[PDB]
Amino acid sequence: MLTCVTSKSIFGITTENCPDGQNLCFKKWYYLNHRYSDITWGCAATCPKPTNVRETIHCCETDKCNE
């Protein structure tokens, strides 16, 4: 099984066991003119493709790799 970060903050780091078939962790955010969106973390079955040029998406395959 795989375990991924699902949210991270100064109050703590949350992880979750991915269900069968979701064998990737991801981390994503958007950037525009020196502003960043909130970061999103989770499990996924396929690496989501960026919906636009402002999005950065990073996927990986081992426990807690998406921190």
Image (tube, grey):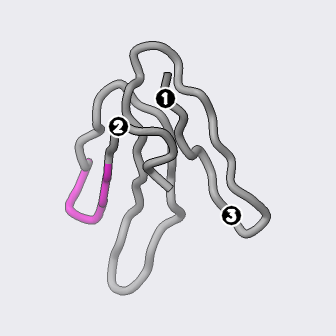
Residue bearing the label numbered 3? 9
Q: Give the CA separation, mark 1 to mark 3.
A: 21 Å
Label 1 sits on what residue type? Answer: Leu
Nearer-N-terminus badge (1/3): 1
How far apart are the two marked residues, 3 and 2, measured between alpha carbons?
22 Å
Q: Give the Cα separation between the discs numbered 1 and 2.
A: 8 Å
**Label annotation for residue 67:** none
Nearest to the observer: residue 34 or residue 24: 24
Horizontally, residue 21 falls left or right of residue 42, namely left
Nearer the observer: mark 3 or 2; the answer is 2
Q: Is residue 11 above or below residue 36?
A: above
Which residues are drawn in magenta? Answer: 51-58
7 or 65: nearer the eye?
A: 65
Q: Is residue 52 magenta?
A: yes
Looking at the image, do the residues carrying marks 1 and 3 touch, with CB atoms under 8 Å apart? no
**In terms of secondary structure, where does tag 3 sit?**
strand
> Quick one: 46 or 66, which is closer to the camera?
66
Q: Residue at x 41, y 23 (%)?
A: 22
Residue 56 highlighted magenta (yes or no): yes
Q: What secondary structure is marked by label 1?
A: loop
Residue at position x 44%, y 51% from top? Answer: 66
Give left or right: position of 4 versus 51. right
Q: Residue beneath label 2, please?
A: 61
Query: Mark 2 or mark 1, which is nearer the start of the sequence?
Result: 1
For badge 2, the amino acid type reads: Glu
User: Badge 1 is on which residue?
Assistant: 2
Counting from the top left corner in percent of width and height, residue 56 is at 30, 60
Point 31% across, 53% down: residue: 57
In the rendered structure, are the residues bearing label 1 and label 2 in contact, judged by CB atoms less than 8 Å apart?
A: yes
